[PDB]
């Protein structure tokens, strides 16, 4: 089997991407944020505290003939940005782009933090990191990908995120029309539950490539590119008037600037992030200070290849016995 679904940016900055997901019988379609840096499939629901729902579409298990309470199971997750949610668990039929899993754990939110409530466009998350990070207790649950894997034509999914445009998540096949050149594969460590890999270095604009190992994660549910302070300082030093602002919480730059590209290494290959992808617009409405898309990881504990990086590439998440990542230009 395979599946193929379009993923759409939630706003004009590509802050996140939503993908329609069918849950239950008859289908309830919710727009979920596919997150390769977490491992819970959780939804706004009929159980979510009413004051914490503002415009989201909810899953109602009582209207699904295939829903079944996973008795005793609870969940609680806290994300890198300080957001969180928690609740109880049902199993139900979940379909993505024509690929169906029966018995998928659907984590029903009883509580969500303010950032979720405030984002009317995201009805929940679909985690695509390793199932070792799944929060369900006392019996850990599998991700949609892990449950689908055995049925897929090939044990892979691919992320093809758009810049200010829709893109695609495919399951079970690699669309050879969706990228240019060849795919370069690189090793993955699953030790921390992530798609963790080591970039071979970077370049700023038309500058020389610096060969240096940068461990980090491929995380579709993080907007920006978080890299070591040395790397990030070297990038923003090439932008007149850029500075790190403790008041704003990262590097800002004049909105009048033209940004340089940023290249990262994948083995001997190179992925180039255009300068425009690193513009996250005014810090507040109407400001002439703009927020940078490359930020320091120094206060995270991990480097994160978020959407800024991943949407410059066709990315293969290879879930074979020995997982690997692949990157191609597009
Ligand atoms: C609501 C907030 O933007 C949000 C937080 C965390 C994730 N995630 O890591 O995928 C998505 C969305
Ligand atoms: Na922000």
Image (spheres, helix red, strand yellow):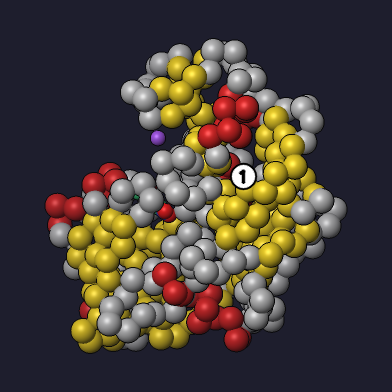
The image quarter containing residue 202 is top right
Q: Residue at x 57, y 63 (%)?
A: 195
- The answer to whether residue 230 of the structure is visible from this angle is yes
Horizontal side of 281 relative to 321 (left or right) equals left
Percent coordinates x, y for residue 79 in the rendering: 36, 54
Horizontal side of 268 relative to 27 (left or right) equals right
Q: Is mark 1 within 8 Å of ligand 1?
A: no
Residue tagged by mark 1?
309
Is label 1 in a helix, a strand or a loop? helix
Q: Residue at x 50, y 36 (%)?
A: 296
- The answer to whether residue 220 of the structure is visible from this angle is no
| Quadrant of the drawing holding the N terminus | bottom right
Q: Residue at x 46, y 23 (%)?
A: 244
Q: Residue at x 49, y 50 (%)?
A: 302
Horizontal side of 62 relative to 237 (left or right) equals left
Percent coordinates x, y for residue 267 in the rendering: 77, 54
Out of 31 and 126, give the one closest to the viewer: 126
Out of 117 and 261, give the one closest to the viewer: 261
Percent coordinates x, y for residue 25 in the rendering: 37, 81
């Amino acid at each position: 089997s395979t599946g193929s679904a379009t993923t759409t940016p939630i706003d004009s900055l590509d802050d996140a991407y939503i993908t329609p997901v069918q849950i239950g019988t008859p289908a309830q379609t919710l727009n979920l944020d596919f997150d390769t840096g977490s491992s819970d499939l959780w939804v706004f629901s009929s159980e979510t505290t009413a004051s914490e729902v503002d415009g989201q579409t909810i899953y109602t298990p009582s209207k699904s003939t295939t829903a079944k309470l996973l008795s005793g199971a609870t969940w609680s997750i806290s994300y890198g940005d300080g957001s969180s949610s928690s609740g109880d668990v049902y199993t139900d039929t979940v379909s993505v782009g024509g690929l169906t899993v029966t018995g998928q754990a659907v984590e029903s939110a009883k509580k969500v933090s303010s950032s979720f409530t405030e984002d009317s466009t995201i009805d929940g998350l679909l985690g695509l990191a390793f199932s070792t990070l799944n929060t369900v207790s006392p019996t850990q649950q599998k991700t949609f990908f892990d449950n689908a894997k055995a049925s897929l034509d090939s044990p892979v999914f691919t992320a093809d995120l758009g810049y200010h445009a829709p893109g695609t998540y495919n399951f079970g096949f690699i669309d050879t029309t969706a990228y240019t050149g060849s795919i370069t594969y690189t090793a993955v460590s699953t030790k921390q539950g992530f798609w963790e890999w080591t970039s071979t270095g970077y370049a700023v604009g038309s500058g020389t490539f610096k060969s240096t190992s940068i461990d980090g994660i491929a995380d579709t549910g993080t907007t920006l590119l978080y890299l070591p302070a040395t790397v990030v300082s070297a990038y923003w030093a090439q932008v007149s008037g850029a500075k790190s602002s403790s008041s704003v919480g990262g590097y800002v730059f004049p909105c009048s600037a033209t940004l340089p590209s940023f290249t990262f290494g994948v083995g001997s290959a190179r992925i180039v992030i255009p300068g425009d992808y690193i513009d996250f617009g005014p810090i507040s409405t109407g400001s002439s200070s703009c927020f940078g898309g490359i930020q320091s990881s120094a206060g995270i504990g991990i480097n994160i290849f978020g959407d800024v990086a991943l949407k410059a590439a066709f990315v293969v998440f290879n879930g074979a016995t020995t997982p690997t990542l692949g990157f191609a230009s597009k």
